[PDB]
Length: 109
Length: 109
Image 1: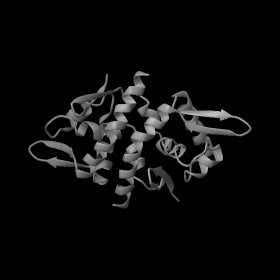
Image 2: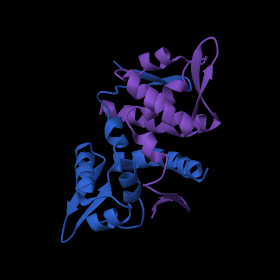
Image 3: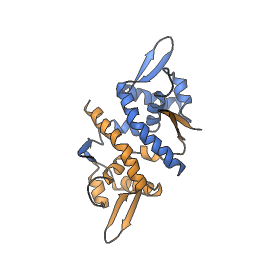
């Protein structure tokens, strides 16, 4: 059974028990997606962790795995190991930024 | 300390330890905001709960309180008790819908 959400002339169908929304909601996931689209270069694990105040290596690693499994992030193992958003991950980030922008406005009051 | 997220020519500042992002990420919160903007009439508690597969009364009540406290939802106590988004809650919903739309696309593969 699904939640049906009005969006203009359309309804969006989400299954709360099976949706990538679950992953997206877990602490840090939206921030990981957001930072992976910062700067000009693939980032290593330390770059990512340093960019998110307070995230543990364990949580970062667990979220990265779930993100790779969900097809939103990929790891490149070269002479260094780096991470980047896939086309799908970049699409998510694109829809995320206006939400985060407004959140920042709310956080100011 | 803050996460700084690139958004076009701007950077969005989010404090991961103090942001309404925390609430927004908790299970069901985005779905509660979304359903509160469905239909044509203020909804009662049962209307809301019935619209989100599997949410418990306890979780729904706890999220509604946090949403009221954060200024995104208000309760009207009249001959019946109903809930609606505030101007701020509707702004959140507005930024949320494209994200949820794309999530639904991802859920299909």
